[PDB]
Image 1 (tube, chains in turn brown, purple):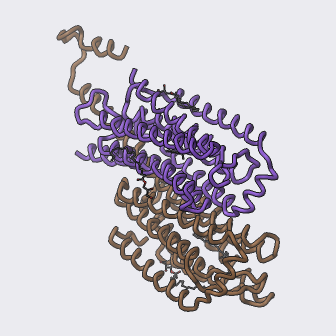
Image 2 (cartoon, rainbow over the protein chains, first blue to last red; image 1 turned 180 degrees about the vertical axis):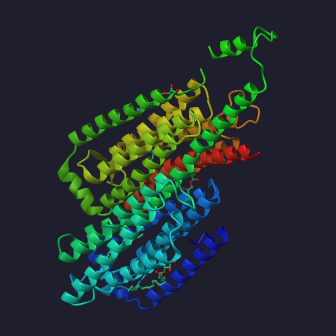
Image 3 (cartoon, each protein chain N blue to C red; image 1 turned 30 degrees about the vertical axis):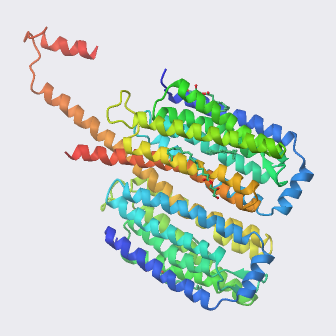
Length: 310
Length: 278
Ligand SMILES: CCCCCCCC/C=C\CCCCCCCC(=O)OC[C@H](O)CO
Ligand SMILES: CCCCCCCC/C=C\CCCCCCCC(=O)OC[C@H](O)CO
Ligand SMILES: CCCCCCCC/C=C\CCCCCCCC(=O)OC[C@H](O)CO
Ligand SMILES: *C/C=C(C)/C=C/C=C(C)/C=C/C1=C(C)CCCC1(C)C
Ligand SMILES: *C/C=C(C)/C=C/C=C(C)/C=C/C1=C(C)CCCC1(C)C
């Protein structure tokens, strides 16, 4: 329920990039390039997996900068503003993940890397996307910062659960998953309470589209805990798990933009509903000013119009 | 006379693009050599990953045009995104098949690299359609379009046949195809020009500004392929480098069109509710 202006979405956007331009430098300071080259060789397709995701996110932002300029309203404008920066961070993250010497941690389950840059992306992105849901539905400013902060610590636990021994990993990882359902349960009830046809303040998106948001987010964010579960269990390869993470990272953020584009293209029907009513009352005003009986000015006035409808 | 389309006509034109490609996919699985394809994806490990990534990029790019079709401003700006909804879908199933199927290919005489006929069979189905599609954004002669459409169809074929020829003739058949490429592009730049006139007889379904963008998007995005194969056959870049460029250039040329229809449809609604405020 922030109801922020375009200059606020710029101020939050420059904060995300400077709080990122600090994160990358932090992860470049602790770099061990001998092992980064060793990991980017033992797992060959990684530099291609992440480099392909960065290019895919480059066009993802271009689709938002078009939706931002050509936005139908100033309400839907500031919504594509947050997605413009959230998807831009996804591109500079995977660009650096695929070309830079970054900091990662050995995990206890299988000895795999923990990219931390991608975790540092989600802790910058995922809280913002829940604040984004706090505007498409206009929930309470507290009920949003609840799940917003609960989802930030959520990602942190699953990151700092890979280092832990067997049992404290299971218990910290299971603690993050329980918090996940909390975020997805409050959201489904956050949009569901905004979809009611009797709801002030009327949401900046149509009522039906909110169901698409609480559907797309639920069944796209669920992939990440499902991959970290299987891969730690040892039931899928590391790269096969990384490939899913890169595509799920794409479908989750891009899925919102295509819904924003869908909404901006749907107000055209709303325009064509207003055009109908205007031309209906316009023909109504003429009937309220004419007299329709035997007033012979062409034929009888009534049959002239009746022949027109015939 | 001129060049027009209709919704049900692009629907049957759409399903013709897929059945002439389904036939193509069968022929290339039929003549394929799986023992030789395994060697390709072995030496070039990133090939299978590139195509599968390109396919994912095109899967979403198709669905964006479906939203432009159901929520189109005009009956003509519908049958324009309709062509792209089939063009961009072929790219999704072409790259999904290139990354997951045993396909037929050829060894080029220049450097022994593979020549992906499935991709060549994609452009032969795409490029002549986008030029029929360019005959609807500008409404050129059905003869002026049939020329470039059949000249671009043989253009991609000549560049494919050039790989199998010896030294001397491959030079001239390749150069003979690039000479026709400029013939296609020169006719396009002047094809939008006739419609870009503020006093044109059949008003084009696009504004004058959006038409100059198209003749710039199609010039600067299509010129990459004749530069990739050039710098790859000469040996100035690795094969996988030219494939990654071909995997990105193939996305820009077709999503560049998809984002023009979005911005024009969006520019139309914002202009229309303004004309309602007044
Ligand atoms: C253990 C993983 C370590 C990774 C290594 C890099 C860490 C840097 C990442 C984030 C910095 C914190 C800045 C963002 C903090 C967001 C907290 C939050 O939830 O804010 C929501 C907001 O209240 C909605 O209105
Ligand atoms: C009716 C438009 C159909 C366009 C193609 C869709 C099917 C593409 C499949 C194979 C193309 C093989 C090469 C075909 C060469 C183009 C044929 C042509 O000249 O069409 C011009 C049309 O008359 C201008 O209105
Ligand atoms: C000026 C154009 C006026 C309007 C006409 C529109 C049509 C343009 C179409 C093709 C032009 C040539 C395509 C680009 C070919 C460049 C090849 C080249 O210059 O090669 C340099 C060399 O490869 C370095 O490494
Ligand atoms: C754009 C990136 C997004 C939306 C990432 C979302 C991640 C989640 C919704 C959940 C992640 C995890 C858990 C629920 C538990 C284990 C740790 C994670 C990060 C895999
Ligand atoms: C969607 C796919 C498109 C737009 C493909 C376009 C291909 C070209 C514009 C050109 C291709 C070639 C040449 C000009 C010369 C050598 C042969 C080709 C196919 C590389």
